[PDB]
Image: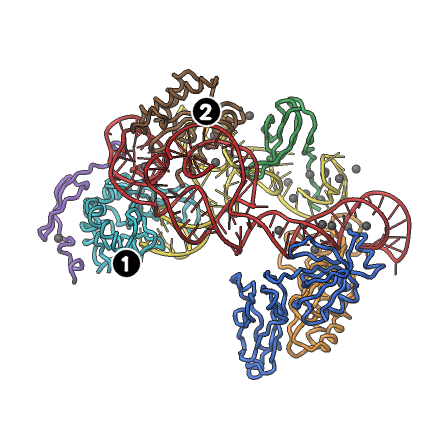
Chain colours: A blue, B cyan, C purple, D green, E orange, F brown, G yellow, H red
Amino acid sequence: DFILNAQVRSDLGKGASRRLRRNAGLVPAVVYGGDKEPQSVTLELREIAKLLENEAAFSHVIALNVGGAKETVLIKALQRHPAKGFVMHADFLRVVADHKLTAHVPLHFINEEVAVGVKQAGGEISHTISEVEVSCLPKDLPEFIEVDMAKVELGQIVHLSDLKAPKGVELVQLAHGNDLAVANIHASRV
Amino acid sequence: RLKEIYRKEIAPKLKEELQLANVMEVPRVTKITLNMGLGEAVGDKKIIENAVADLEKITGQKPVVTYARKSIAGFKIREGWPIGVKVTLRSDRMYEFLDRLLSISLPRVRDFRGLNAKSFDGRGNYSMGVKEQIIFPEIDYDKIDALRGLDITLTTTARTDDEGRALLRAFKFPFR
Amino acid sequence: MKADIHPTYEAIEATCSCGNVIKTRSTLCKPIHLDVCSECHPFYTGK
Amino acid sequence: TRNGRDSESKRLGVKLFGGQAVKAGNILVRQRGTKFHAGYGVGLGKDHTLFAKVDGVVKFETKGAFGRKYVSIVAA
Amino acid sequence: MLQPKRTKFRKQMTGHNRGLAHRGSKVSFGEYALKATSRGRLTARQIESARRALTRHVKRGGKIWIRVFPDKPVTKKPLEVRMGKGKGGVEYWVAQIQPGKVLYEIEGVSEELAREAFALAAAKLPLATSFVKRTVM
Amino acid sequence: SVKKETRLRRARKARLKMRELETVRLCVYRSSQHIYAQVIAADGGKVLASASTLDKDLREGATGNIDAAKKVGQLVAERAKAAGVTQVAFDRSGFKYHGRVKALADAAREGGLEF
RNA sequence: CCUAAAGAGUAACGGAGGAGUACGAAGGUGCGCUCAGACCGGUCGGAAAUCGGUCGCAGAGUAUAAAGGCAAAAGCGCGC
RNA sequence: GCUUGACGAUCAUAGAGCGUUGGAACCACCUGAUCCCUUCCCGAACUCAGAAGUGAAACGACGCAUCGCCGAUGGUAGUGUGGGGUCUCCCCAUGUGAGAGUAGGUCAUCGUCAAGC
Ligand SMILES: [Mg+2]
Ligand SMILES: [Mg+2]
Ligand SMILES: [Mg+2]
Ligand SMILES: [Mg+2]
Ligand SMILES: [Mg+2]
Ligand SMILES: [Mg+2]
Ligand SMILES: [Mg+2]
Ligand SMILES: [Mg+2]
Ligand SMILES: [Mg+2]
Ligand SMILES: [Mg+2]
Ligand SMILES: [Mg+2]
Ligand SMILES: [Mg+2]
Ligand SMILES: [Mg+2]
Ligand SMILES: [Mg+2]
Ligand SMILES: [Mg+2]
Ligand SMILES: [Mg+2]
Ligand SMILES: [Mg+2]
Ligand SMILES: [Mg+2]
Ligand SMILES: [Mg+2]
Ligand SMILES: [Mg+2]
Ligand SMILES: [Mg+2]
Ligand SMILES: [Mg+2]
Ligand SMILES: [Mg+2]
Ligand SMILES: [Zn+2]
């Protein structure tokens, strides 16, 4: 499931880190956060690359296992090769039972076939954004935020305030007094 | 004078009519500034000191000539050239000009049911225009030059125009 | 107030047609006879 | 072409660095304007030149509001 | 042909093209993209040529973004002209491309149709390319 | 306020010169009711001699006028002498050197210390 | 000013601009003061004149190109 | 030990905003313009003589992270020396190592003198 294995990294630097990717086939990583000193760990590339095609990979909670001591983490940021695209570095944020945390949550758009602006007016659908910054307690962190586009007419805009959210979830950008277009309907290009 | 009228009845009645908690925050009027923008005399320069005398007798106080802050050839003017004159009044001298303005001159202008009660900036100040200078006494109609539009501004210590207008309801301003 | 650069300022009088006498210091040095004032102007009365 | 012009270099910059011993009248920095301001023991020439007025050691401190960079002379 | 409406200076030095593209290498607006896997420079006539080939194939709906803008002038000295005597006049405009830069984006079409259209465009460009989907991060 | 902030900007130029020259400064402060005088050592660090109308021989009320400041000006000179100081510079601290501050200064000169 | 490779210097028929003056006050000193701009209110002028208020902090200014400076303003006004 | 006033050290982890509060003393607004003095007009500002009112404005203190400002660990880019390749560009050994971003922090900390408890 959401299981990752790690070993304690000891050699730090550019030359040491370039050697892991070339010979050992491992990936440097960091486990910071919580109330502890940060820990530098390493993990195998073919295992992190297999957890990353799960759709709810970043918005779920991982069970990291460093050596024989396991704990609760979350994919906080990720580094990829600009050209090839594989992952080079990754950092994990520790999860505390009573502490607010932030995450990136993808949006599950639904029932676009029977939208009023598409079935009747013959318009298109454009997803302006595909994830939203959220902030919530770990116990109620959603896998996806569901946006419903059934009763949408041609030219009608959908903003952050339009979509619903589960309990105890803030949209961060909305809290900053900045709601922005999520999706819209418009006439065909040609 | 109007000094006696403000600090014995006008101020105490406004104290409860705005429901103000403190005495010092009761609104008051500080200064009256008149000027007149002489868009003429761009090539004349003779009427500048003529309009000085006109505004000198109206107030009993010498005016000062205000200069152009920028050239802008659209009005055919240039920096350092005189555009207008101005006066500023305070304390007793503006409670005696007001009384003459209140009713010796405002009734005899030509017309009007009242004054526009909507000429208030967002901060509680009132400014009114005057079309003909002859509305005042102390200037004979038979001796003046061409008519010119004196101007009036009332600067008050009002937070907003609600108590600013309320203060001008006192002194029984002619508001239509 | 500076010295001797301003016109004379005296109390004088002001008498209106409606039997109104008002004291007001101004620069005429002579009593005046008026024709209108608030005690007699139409729009100051209700018309 | 209508471009082939330039001007002689003026040899500007710091002449004595932090810690160097100085004498009275020694030129410390040559400037256009004042990248550096005259601190304690230093004077300002009419072309914005910093020269020593006492004997000591260059300091090169930045302090005060405005984030100014000061050149001062201290005890040796 | 894309080119800036006005420029501060008419000419530029040749410069050098170095480094990978850490900025401009993410699928930001669209949902499928054509990334560059080799470095070079597009001449603003290939950018224009490769855009006919991409919108013509979809020919039904879809939104297309162009993430490359040619803003660097280049000069060519005329024929039968010696060396020196100034710098040549501006001929055309190019764009510096580094490995990993995303060139074209598209959405509102099937994944299979996106692959066809981006192969039409890539044949007009003088550098290696790739097909990239979109990720959360 | 606008009034105090503007004055404290007026006072700035004179005080900057007096630390470049590293001279002992006689600083005066004038309020609506009282007036104060301090002898600032060399750079604003320590206060050497000080006097005002608040000491226990001038607490009577006639404290905001010309002849009240004269008694302060002569008194601060005496306390300055006990500290072995002379040849000080006068800081009007942005106030116009015309009235109460001038009376304080002139009394200081008769006190013995020199400007 | 860039080329010029974070001390100085550094070439090309390399890329861009200026000078061959002005000022008896546009210098000295003492004292005093902050600009451009936006909005609102006001007699004709109206997007833009002079006036009042709020915001703003230098996006103004510097005799003259560009660079580097400018609150003790190096910017502005007055007396001697 | 505490409060108020003056002068400094340091220049945002110290600022901005948004709320609460202080008049016994201090400070401020305040009363008046005969005298000193002032306005390219005006006691608005400067100045003088004060003690009837209010802490309304201003100032000070106290709270909050909303903005601002600080900001790690790790990774990445560049780079001196020696050696390589498919040599417009990179790689290896070795030393060095940002900028941006992430977790987070901040509603300052001191010194001298004078008044009141
Ligand atoms: Mg290396
Ligand atoms: Mg040139
Ligand atoms: Mg050239
Ligand atoms: Mg040269
Ligand atoms: Mg040079
Ligand atoms: Mg000199
Ligand atoms: Mg070249
Ligand atoms: Mg870049
Ligand atoms: Mg000055
Ligand atoms: Mg330059
Ligand atoms: Mg150099
Ligand atoms: Mg070098
Ligand atoms: Mg050579
Ligand atoms: Mg020439
Ligand atoms: Mg000058
Ligand atoms: Mg001069
Ligand atoms: Mg205006
Ligand atoms: Mg200043
Ligand atoms: Mg006063
Ligand atoms: Mg930062
Ligand atoms: Mg590091
Ligand atoms: Mg590093
Ligand atoms: Mg950093
Ligand atoms: Zn009448």
Q: In which quarter of the view is residue A187 placed?
A: bottom right
Q: Nearer the viewer, residue H102 or H3?
A: H3
Instruction: Using the image, determine if residue D37 lies above or below residue E63.
Output: above
Q: Residues within 10 Å of mark 1 (few under 14, many from 20)?
A: some
Kindly report the distance in space between the C-alpha atoms of the residues bearing marks 1 and 2.
61 Å
* Farthest left residue in view: C19
Where in the figure is residue H63, as x and y percent of width and height? 48, 51
User: Which residue is at the front of the view, A53 or B46?
Assistant: A53
Badge number at residue B57:
none
Q: Is residue H117 left or right of residue C24?
A: right
Task: Identify whether D10 is placed above or below A92.
Answer: above
- Nearer the viewer's eye, disc 1 or disc 2? 2
Residue type highlighted by circle 1: Asn
Dot 2 alpha-carbon crowd within 10 angstroms: few under 14, some 14 to 19, many 20 or more: many
Circle 1 sits on which residue? Answer: B116
Residue E39 in view here: no
Position of B117 relative to B68 (above/below): below
**Amino acid beneath label 2:** Val
Q: Secondary structure at mark 2?
A: strand
From the viewer's perspective, is H1 left or right of A129? Answer: left
Closer to us: A12 or H77: A12
Q: Is residue A2 visible?
A: yes
Q: Tell me the residue that label 2 is attached to.
A: F39
| Depth order, front residue of A103/D33 | A103
Query: What kind of element bears circle 1?
Result: loop
Label 2 chain ID: F
